[PDB]
Picture: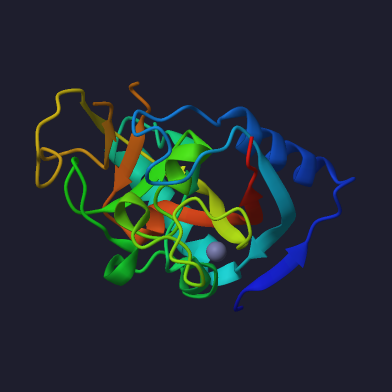
Length: 206
Ligand SMILES: [Zn+2]
């Protein structure tokens, strides 16, 4: 019932689909690569499928709950996640302890539709101290990991202003924050995300 990790063959449709979503969603960030480093491309080392029967059942139960609360619209999206606690997430799921961070859109679990936005969170807020080994936010050596996740958004609060908020208004299951304007997706319950794919990669020096 615990986690099984399956290495995907680069010739597999799933590997190719995930790598292409990861590469195609790279953007040039407003910070000129301060947080996540300077790159236009990833070198994908491997992609692992994450199979956890218990996490999947709880995700499916929560999605049905959210669907019923939002006129049968669970609004599932495939979104990227970066976190220093990725290793814990694939084994134990999104734990509101340590999966939660702060940001412009309040405390919660942060996802992005752009892989390069999630890359800014891999080593912590604003890239933290960068890679453990070289303390380098733009390390081209160290292997990074990010997740590509199934995320139940239900009813989203759309935030567009650069205003610090604590939490979404009542009756909302997520925030979509857009302060260019790359969208960040915040959820408040760990069971609203399933870590489908573990991507091991390097950022490439242009
Ligand atoms: Zn490094």
